[PDB]
Length: 140
Length: 140
Picture 1: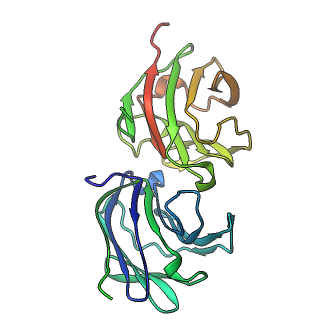
Picture 2 (picture 1 turned 180 degrees about the vertical axis):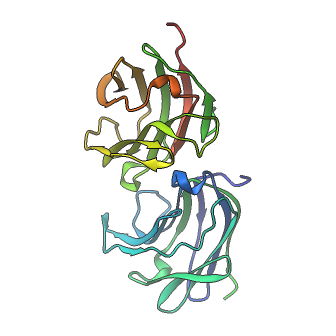
Picture 3 (picture 1 turned 135 degrees about the vertical axis):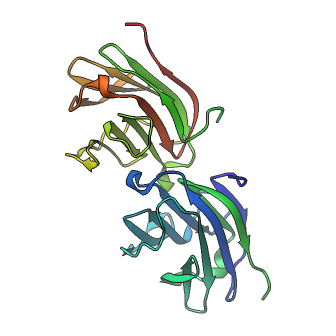
């Protein structure tokens, strides 16, 4: 919407950081729009991905990392708190041992750290959404 | 790019019609951007799809129809004429018995008609591309 998609913001993350994303799918769930959030190690889209979060709305969520160019072990979830046609608020919190993904205030997914969060230099949000808010917290 | 994505144009199709699309992926192929072209039976995104064409750039192409709300038999191809980082020209021709998809001037995919092309009322182009040209021919 207001924010360009693909959306790119330089970022740093550590324990206590939160990434907050407000947006809306561009299609009804029957048409299977997607959402992707990638935490990258460099300011280049081809760089490694410490945390890859990909929603196929209405179907599934997959999480992974891309390390030295290669995708690692996929974690697949059928949990689907996102609501057809609705705006969502996505909150990704950096805990000591994992990322925790909140959807509309409800814990919905977690992913244990495979690479230290301090390796992140960039966050990208893309695929079939409009985006009205993006924030990384830097309070701690 | 110039054209909004998702892109929607009311359309009619018959034998001899050609749909021409010029665009560019929004991501490098390592990041697996997608492209989707859907020929719809009504001016609503939830309507049936006479021809569904979905590219996972660098990996595969799937084609299908959605009839009375339900996806039918998927046709999956590993043919991948699209080039990483490059603009493409996509040409979809309505032949008497099938759609023929040309990529950069080369025949790349075909899909036999399951529903008469005259049932199409709308074309949608969406997912991870920018679009600089869209045309439906009406010469015949």
